[PDB]
Image (cartoon, helix red, strand yellow):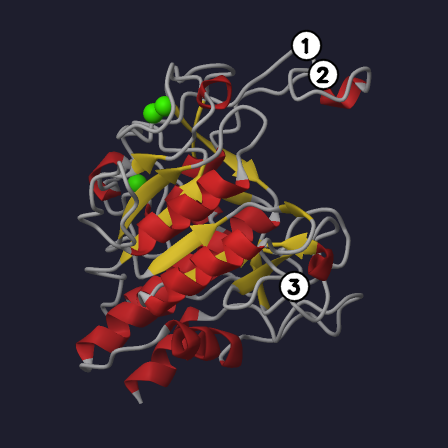
């Protein structure tokens, strides 16, 4: 249905092992009046995002990470997390020497709610929804405490020195994480966000390791997402195991980025792979589900929304080599479930 130039390439919306977002748009549900926060590298000023981006906030405290000249500020612009000369560091490993800017937060944001039916570029899973960019990641990643403050604020939590969020999110997408157990502080903020009514949707990670060995997956009250391929099998790099709740397409995912290698230069589109790409598919479907639930006067708690998403998955291609939740997220079965 969408008129967008490169929609045809987004197999992950509509093909055999896609999320069946097409079958839900056919029902008139697009995630209208749903707000999804993206706790990530920030947002590009991209012709195929602008319309669907709401005021966010920049939680990065170290100015050597943010690359914008100060700590916390009201502008969640992705300056570009590029680096060279082993700035992150790991010298002398040549594979850690340098990286071009990822535009990670925008690729993720486009999956959720890229401007759709405007002819240019691509579509989003919940293109009737809106995105609040919570910038917590810059050069070399981010601090746990910036991430945790950011996710609490995303839900509507007040933080001293930060103007109240006018746009609290029902769904908080965290395409991020690292090695180690969930911290006391991060768990606490997740629990407070969940009590505010937000579903916290997180990436399993990309180290071909048991996702239980990582945060946010090892936290309570998150929905952890593994990555599958166009063939319906576990993508090679996807973390795995009992604490992965479900999976979504995380290989050859087309979305919105910039062509700049350092700072933004011009709007572009690219294929990426990672549980990071899978995660916003689930965040996008969560928003579709909520817009369907709204239409029948049905409120859903984060726990209930998570159960709908996990219980209505489509099957994998055979069994997998590792556990990856119940199936692949399925917007049609998820939405049909809440409409009776
Ligand atoms: Ca700043
Ligand atoms: Ca900023
Ligand atoms: Ca578009």
Q: Position of residue 228 (x, y in %)?
A: 64, 58
Q: Which circle's residue, 3 or 2, is located before the other in the chain?
A: 2
- The disc at residue 97 is 2
Return the x and y of residue 88 as percentages of the image width and height: 66, 22
Q: Earlier in the sequence, mark 3 or mark 1?
A: 1
Outermost residue toward the front in this view: 160
Marks 2 and 1 in Cβ contact (< 8 Å): yes
* Rendering coords of residue 288 (x, y %): 32, 66
Mark 2 crowdedness (10 Å alpha carbons): few <14, some 14-19, many ≥20: some
Question: In the displayed structure, does residue 25 sit left or right of residue 180?
Answer: left
Q: Residue at x 70, y 50 (%)?
A: 180
Vertical comparison of 19 with 56: above or below: below
- Is the CB of mark 3 within 8 Å of ligand 3? no
Q: CA distance from mark 3 to mark 2?
A: 34 Å
The one nearer the camera, 300 or 277, is 300
239 sits left or right of 27 in the view: right
Q: Which of these two is toward me, 328 or 56? A: 56
Q: Is residue 48 left or right of residue 225?
A: left
- Whether residue 294 is visible to the viewer of this picture, yes or no, is yes
Using the rendered image of the protein, determine whether residue 27 is visible from the camera's viewpoint.
no
Q: Is residue 97 left or right of residue 272?
A: right
Mark in the foreground, 3 or 2: 2
Q: Nearer the viewer, residue 32 or 174?
A: 174
Q: Which residue is mark 1?
A: 85
Residue 21, compared with residue 256, is above or below; it is below
In the picture, which quadrant includes the N terminus? bottom left
The image quadrant that residue 28 belongs to is bottom left
Q: Which residue corresponds to mark 3? A: 232
């Amino acid at each position: 249905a969408p008129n967008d130039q490169h929609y045809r390439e987004q197999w992950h919306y509509f093909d055999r092992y896609g999320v069946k977002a097409d079958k839900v748009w056919d029902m008139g549900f697009t995630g209208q009046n749903v707000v999804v926060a993206v706790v990530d590298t920030g947002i590009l000023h991209h012709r195929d995002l602008n319309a669907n981006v709401l005021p966010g906030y920049d939680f990065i405290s170290n100015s050597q990470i943010s690359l914008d000249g100060d700590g916390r500020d009201a502008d969640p612009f992705d300056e570009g997390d590029w680096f060279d000369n082993w700035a992150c560091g790991g010298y002398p490993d040549p594979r850690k020497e340098r990286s071009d800017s990822s535009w990670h937060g925008s690729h993720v944001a486009g999956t959720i709610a890229a401007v759709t039916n405007n002819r240019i570029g691509v579509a989003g899973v919940a293109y009737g929804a809106k995105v609040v960019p919570v910038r917590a990641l810059g050069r070399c990643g981010g601090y746990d405490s910036d991430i945790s403050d950011g996710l609490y604020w995303a839900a509507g939590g007040r933080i001293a020195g930060i103007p109240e969020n006018r746009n609290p999110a029902k769904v908080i997408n965290m395409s991020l994480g690292s090695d180690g157990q969930c911290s006391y502080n991060a768990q606490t903020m997740i629990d407070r966000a969940t009590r505010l009514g937000a579903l916290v949707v997180v990436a399993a990670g990309n180290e071909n390791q048991n996702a239980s060995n990582t945060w946010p997956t090892s936290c309570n009250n998150v929905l952890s997402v593994g990555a599958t391929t166009s063939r319906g099998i576990r993508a090679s790099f996807s973390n795995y195991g009992v604490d992965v709740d479900l999976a979504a397409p995380g290989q050859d995912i087309l979305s919105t980025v910039d062509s700049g290698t350092r700072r933004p230069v011009s709007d572009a589109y690219s294929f990426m792979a990672g549980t990071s790409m899978a995660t916003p598919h689930v965040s996008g479907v969560a928003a579709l589900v909520i817009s369907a639930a709204n239409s029948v006067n049905k409120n859903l708690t984060p726990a209930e929304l998570k159960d709908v998403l996990v219980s209505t998955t489509s099957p994998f291609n055979g069994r997998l080599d590792r556990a990856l939740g119940s199936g692949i997220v399925d917007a049609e079965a998820a939405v049909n479930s809440v409409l009776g």
